[PDB]
Image (cartoon, rainbow, N blue to C red):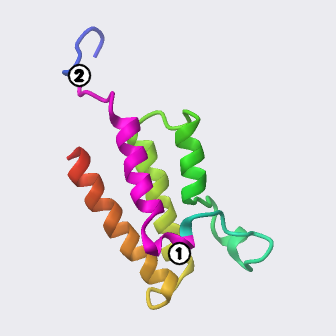
Amino acid sequence: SMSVKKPKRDDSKDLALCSMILTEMETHEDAWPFLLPVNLKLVPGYKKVIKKPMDFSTIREKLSSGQYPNLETFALDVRLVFDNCETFNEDDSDIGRAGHNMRKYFEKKWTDTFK
C-alpha cells in the first residue's frame, strides 16, 4: 500500500525472454495456422464469431513496438490465439490439433522460463 512495497522481482530481461519464446513458437512446424491474421474476407463466420482475433505476427509487432506493458499481457495474447483456435476448430482437425500442440509447447516454455 502507500509507501509499503513488496520486494522488486527483476523484470529487465522479460522483453528479451518473451522475444525468444515467440521465436520458438514462430519456428515450430505446427505454427502455420497462427503466423498471420485470419483473412476475414475469406473465412466465413470468423469475423462475427471471434471477437478478438490474434495471431503471432500481430503479437510480434506489439512486442516490437512497446505495446505490452508486462509479461502477463503478452501471455494473454498468446493464449487468445489458442482460445480462438479452440472456439472455431474441431479438436479432431489438423488446425485444432495444431492449436492444442502449440498451447502445450508455449505453456512449458513459459513455466520453464519464468516460474
Q: Residue at x 60, y 45 (%)?
A: 61
Q: Nearer the viewer, mark 2 or mark 1?
A: 2
Instruction: Find residue 66 and report its horizontal and vertical position in percent.
Output: 54, 33
Task: Give the tally of numbered discs.
Answer: 2
Furthest residue toward top: 3
Considering only order in the chain, which callout, 1 or 2, is on the residue closer to the N terminus?
2
Mark 2 nearby-residue class (10 Å; few <14, some 14–19, many ≥20): few
Q: Image quadrant of residue 29?
A: bottom left
Asked which quadrant contains residue 39, the reply is bottom right
Secondary structure mostly seen in the magenta stretch: helix
In the rendered image of this protein, does residue 94 appear above or below residue 76?
below
Residue drawn at (32%, 33%), measured in percent from left and top?
A: 13
- The image shows residue 5, relative to residue 102, as above or below, that is above
Magenta span: 8-33
Between the residue at mark 2 and the residue at mark 1, the CA separation in whole angstroms equals 38 Å
| Residue at x 39% of width, y 69% of height | 102
Tell me if residue 32 is in the magenta stretch: yes
In the picture of the structure, the residue carrying the numbered disc 2 is 8
Q: Which mark is residue 87?
A: 1
Percent from the top left, x then y, of residue 104?
Answer: 32, 69
Label annotation for residue 18 = none
- Image: 77 above or below 69: below
Residue 1 shown left or right of residue 51 in the figure: left
| Residue nearer the viewer, 4 or 93 | 93
Q: Position of residue 58 (x, y in %)?
A: 60, 52
Q: Amino acid at mark 1?
A: Thr
